[PDB]
Image (cartoon, coloured by chain):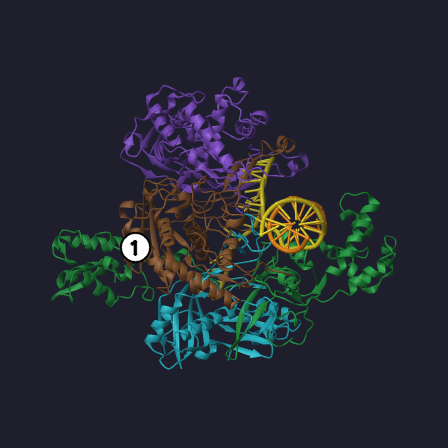
Chain colours: A cyan, B green, C brown, D purple, E yellow, F orange
Amino acid sequence: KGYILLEKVNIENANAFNNIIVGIPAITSFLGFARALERKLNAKEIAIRINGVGLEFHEYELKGYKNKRGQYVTSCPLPGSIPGQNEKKLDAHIMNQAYIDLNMSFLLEVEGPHVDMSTCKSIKSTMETLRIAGGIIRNYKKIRLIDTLADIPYGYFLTLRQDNLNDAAGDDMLDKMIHALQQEDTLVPIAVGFKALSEVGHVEGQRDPEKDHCFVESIFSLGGFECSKILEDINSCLWRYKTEEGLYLCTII
Amino acid sequence: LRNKILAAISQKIPEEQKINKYIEGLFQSIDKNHLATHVAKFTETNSPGNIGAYDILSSDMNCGYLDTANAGWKEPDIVTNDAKYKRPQGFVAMEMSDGRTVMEHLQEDSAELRHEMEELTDKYDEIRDGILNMPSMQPYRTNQFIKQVFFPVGGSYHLLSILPSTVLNYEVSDRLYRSKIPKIRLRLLSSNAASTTGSRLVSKNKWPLVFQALPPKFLEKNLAKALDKEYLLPDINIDELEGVDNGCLIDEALLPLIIDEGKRKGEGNYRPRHLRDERKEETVQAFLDKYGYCNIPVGYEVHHIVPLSQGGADSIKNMIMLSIEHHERVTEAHASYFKW
Amino acid sequence: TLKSRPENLSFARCLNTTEAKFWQTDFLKRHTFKLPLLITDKAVLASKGHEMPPDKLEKEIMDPNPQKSQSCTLSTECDTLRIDFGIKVLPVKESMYSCSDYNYRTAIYQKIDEYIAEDGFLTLAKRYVNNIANARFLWRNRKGAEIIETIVTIEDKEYPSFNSKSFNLDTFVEDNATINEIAQQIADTFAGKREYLNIYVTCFVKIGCAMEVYPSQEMTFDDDDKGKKLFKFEGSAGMHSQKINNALRTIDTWYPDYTTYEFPIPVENYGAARSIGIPFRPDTKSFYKLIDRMILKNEDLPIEDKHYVMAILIRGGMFSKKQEK
Amino acid sequence: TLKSRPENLSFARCLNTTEAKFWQTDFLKRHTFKLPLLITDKAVLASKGHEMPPDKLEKEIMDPNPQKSQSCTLSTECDTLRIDFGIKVLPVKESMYSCSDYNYRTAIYQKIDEYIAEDGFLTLAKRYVNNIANARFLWRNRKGAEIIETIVTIEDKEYPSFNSKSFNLDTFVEDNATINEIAQQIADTFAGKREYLNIYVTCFVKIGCAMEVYPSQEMTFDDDDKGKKLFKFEGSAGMHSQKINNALRTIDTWYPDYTTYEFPIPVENYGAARSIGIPFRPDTKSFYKLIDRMILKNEDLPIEDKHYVMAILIRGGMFSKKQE
DNA sequence: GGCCTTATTAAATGACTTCTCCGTACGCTTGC
DNA sequence: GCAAGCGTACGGA
């Protein structure tokens, strides 16, 4: 096992909008990016597998401006032609969207036979073809192996906070989020994963006709920020996949 | 009251025909509409037909996560494929004399509503039965316009189709309207676009409030942070200075120019150590390569015309090579000026 | 045989472009000197002069009218605008992020390999590089400048400065050696002979002291501020990435009416071009009809139509079957 | 053929103008010496002198009234104000920023070419150069100056300075050689015989020692500071580009009532002067009906209406017509 | 170690731009 | 002769 840090990656126009949330993308966006990097490396026979991800924020800019009342107003790109019945017209409908620019460093937890500088160079040659949450990777400082929590450059990790959510005032789960956020100003809501709305099956129109399919609702939770100088166990920030009988979950273990 | 509201919506036709027109359109439209809590047409209006789900569950009230099962959304959503069948969603939303909805009075079969409707149509029993027995919206297909996402399961991948939730969107947009939480309003849907999503709640909630899940405010990008990551270069060219050759200062007489260039660029542009450029051996090697050295010649040192602590870039365009004594003199002058 | 298009064909954009910052400088110091360029707030008092019906006009005609706005101006000391932006090119075949029919996937790969045999991608790569060389991405900022220079940097090699004012925007140049070399690098990237290519562009526009500069407007919807809002990028002025990309995509001179409309247009599925109120490719020349004719009916389209089709594949988009209930 | 004006129609500003920066100087030294002129914060104890109804008046009539403010004043050593600003002229023909009907674009280009055949753009250019020589852009600063010297520089040629006191603002001079030489270059630029023309001007106003100076005031929208805020450009005082451009646009002597008023108004879509609260061209000669009559009805308008129309096209604007 | 001043007042008159951002069945018309 | 393409109301906190 070993740990690879992707240091200070700059992302343009990450998809910032979720059904309940505008801002930080879904956690599944980042972990799916890491899985796509795994698949790209494996298709080159580097045979690395990536078991978990640590997300450290360094800068952000939501595409928008602050009102004099301090609230953000979200920008859109002018939409092009949208397929369907009205696609020929020069003016096309505007749907709900928001976009965020991120400066971020990714910790990866890695299995492989040859975890070394050659596989770092392979990640370097691979990462240029990928996207993060639909955003374009403009630039990155370095890709390197690390051994200790003193190696990470100063920044803030994002970690799960199920305790604060469950301990909130018990009227309702949305009320638990509201009261928790109103008591703990540093915490933020995040989309964590997906709940099956229907039993696994095959349906017409699939992206792939041959991989089993679910309809799902997004799951949300409460998370919070920890300075990398204040982390104690590296495992305390490693997001990993989990599945439970129709729940699809990112989580920290 | 109620008959006047019904009349007020129905166009400009003479009175008796326009009421009958509204009841005829209502009775035709009821069968086309479904009861649901998730609506595929909310993410993109172009997905054909009714796609959506009606989540009955309630168990997860302390599982540490939020969804439409374990949050108390109060209003059931009603959805249609096409805005021209939308009338029952308006009909049901009207308020009677007590200010309660037609939905409540229908569930009660209240004598007031029965009396009101029976004065306008004999079809009231069938209208009520149709409204109360609307089918649940069932997913039966998928489209290019629904967001379809692979999720790993045991090294296999399941193909998730993400449906947005309208009951939660209405509920959150309501509750954030009455709370101090940091929140953003999305204001993007037009009324026409919102209508063609075919939801009742989306027509009510065309411009929703949503949680502002952003990093801590000190991490926002600003010009001060941006300028701290852009680096200074000197204005002289070591390839054109008479008295420089092969990147090395050959004339002593230019030293006040190099000192003054360092001073002029450096003033107020201090960078703390963690933000400075690293002096890279690759840069020194590429400098030496440009002028054909294998190594720094005997008795010389490579100097940055703008010091790296004072904004200078670690680049070929910022380097110059000096003799040890001239290097000492320039270093001493810069230390004296910048108070190192 | 292939009956119809697949249920979920999707192409990622192959010619990605990043947001551009503006900087300001003095032309003779442009290689070393740069200062930030700031978006400044500038509220404005107007007369009411829009077209009004006469019964409203006689009530409104003399009223004053305040308006909010933002505007951007060089300093009184600088005279040259500077733009820095990046480009990333990806191979065409590998950018097909989805397709739900392996038979169709085989067919489209076969036709792309045929096009690589006919052209590689060199003619399209030349036209894209020519739109970098034209400095067309300046948009309104091009409308007057004394001197313009474009510098293209590829993997830390710096090519010579284009005198971008020497090109006519209506005409693409086949024989400029630097355009040819960069076009070969891009064509090699599109064909899959490399997995990626990074291109960094610097451009200098010598406008004049205190002259106005035009970043792209935001599109935002707000209850109060209908006034003009400009794009701040990291606090400095910038251009939206989509507007630079839309500048590069103006390669197309193949649409059928071209002998009567001698200007190029943006590559689009129906030839929609926002400067003209009519799509230039309805009906038989529209992209859907051409790709269906090329893959379902296996017709050997003339090379201009292959140029257009492959240019739309480079554009990327969502290209499924017309969806059904 | 042409049924109506397009869904979208926009013209870019052809007479682009910079912000203006103020400087202060002593007039004898003026070619060699300039200092920044700063804006000073003030707050002021007014009286409640506004018109009050009697029930309010008898309760508040004597009260003091503190107010926020700003002001600009020359030093006690300098005696002349200096204004630096630039102009950047662009071709009128190539200014059409958006359209939605290529027939309409062809028609408007045909009419501009017809105008360039009937006349140069010279007859407008001479009036714009007159409004430079008039120093109308001084606005309130022109009142009671001792001597006003305007210097026009075009790409490192400096033209002989204008004695701006000598021009009656109600008249446009046709035969001044320097005005004609500048106006020829402007006319060549508008006709598209040149790609651009950068004009810089320096205007010296000898006011008097320590006297007040009037930069353009900022707009405010119920902001918490309701008090007078003045425009700062690069920290020194300045004028908005809008207000100088408006001063230059005061060329119009073709509105119908002119023989009863005999003064030029700002070129405007309805001829709405602001110094006099009656519009001079509602209805029959409003811009919309003149351009529609010139293009849609293809009628050969008299040359003074073409002058006005082309002056609005020089101004630029949005002329989009909603289609039923 | 003690303390951080008492009154009075916060203006008037006008204005807040125009354009685009709708899916669909229903059935009538043109193309293969 | 049969199916694809196009103009139009329809509907609404």
Is residue D229 placed above or below A192 in the rendered structure? above
Packing grade of label 1 (10 A; few <14, some 14-19, many >=20) is: some
Is residue D134 placed above or below A119 in the rendered structure? above
Residue B317 rendering spot, x and y as whole percentages: 24, 57
Q: C202 or D149, which is in the foreground?
A: C202
- How many labels sit on residues? 1
Q: Chain of mark 1?
A: C
Q: Quadrant of residue B244?
A: bottom left
Q: Quadrant of residue D165?
A: top left
Q: D179 or D60, which is in the foreground?
A: D179
Residue B2 rendering spot, x and y as whole percentages: 81, 52
Query: In the image, B289: left or right of C226?
Result: left
Q: C63 or A241, which is in the foreground?
A: A241
Query: In the image, C272: left or right of C115?
Result: right
Q: Which residue is mark 1?
A: C181
Q: C67 or B51, which is in the foreground?
A: B51
Quadrant in the picture for the C terminus of chain D:
top right
Residue C120 rendering spot, x and y as whole percentages: 36, 58
Q: Which residue is painted at 34% across and 56% down in the image?
A: C200
